[PDB]
Image (cartoon, coloured by chain):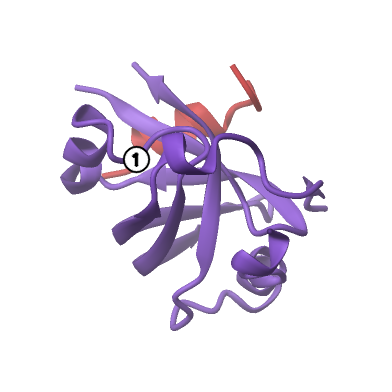
Amino acid sequence: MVGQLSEGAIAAIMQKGDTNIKPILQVINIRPITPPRYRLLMSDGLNTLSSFMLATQLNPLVEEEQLSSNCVCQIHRFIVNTLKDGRRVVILMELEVLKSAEAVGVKIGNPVPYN
Amino acid sequence: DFANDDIDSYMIAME
């Protein structure tokens, strides 16, 4: 099932800062930071990365439970913000949920944290 | 609370 995810997309974002790609990613976890701001742990099958942030305009996808842990989504627009210390925050601007959490049911594959 | 670091604070300060 890992062939369903854009393996290598997290490394490409973190090395190249590519924003043209439309990677297919699995949500591993979502958590609100305190009008909620959602931080996402995402997987591309090979790696996870925890510095994804949901743009406020996408909050309805969480509020209506379309975007939830274990779902698979395709990113259609995102921005990278590189911190002074070199870590990168990935702001998800537009996305489509391709397969619901219920339909997927579990983490895909055995991704390891990016470093 | 995965990755409970200072990235939360950065994302708060954004926008």
Q: What is the x, y in percent for residue A51?
A: 56, 44
Q: Identify the residue under disc 1.
A: A67
A88 relative position to A37: left or right: right
Residue beneath the point at 51% across and 70% down: A23
Circle 1 SS class: loop
The quadrant of the picture occupied by the N terminus of chain A is bottom right
A105 relative position to A8: left or right: left
Q: What is the x, y in percent for residue A75?
A: 40, 65
* Position above or below: A105 against B4: below
* Position above or below: A94 against A28: below
Q: Nearer the viewer, residue A72 or A13?
A: A72
A20 relative position to A51: left or right: left
Residue beneath the point at 81% across and 46% down: A110
Q: Which hue is chain B drawn in?
A: red
Q: Which chain is in purple here?
A: A
Residue beneath the point at 65% across and 47% down: A49
Going by the numbered disc 1, the residue's amino acid type is Leu
Return the chain for callout 1.
A
Q: Residues within 10 Å of mark 1 (few under 14, many from 20)?
A: many
Q: What is the x, y in percent for residue A83?
A: 57, 52
A2 relative position to A40: left or right: right
Q: What is the x, y in percent for residue B14?
A: 34, 42
Residue beneath the point at 44% across and 37% down: A101
* Position above or below: A49 against A36: below
* Position above or below: A19 against A67: below
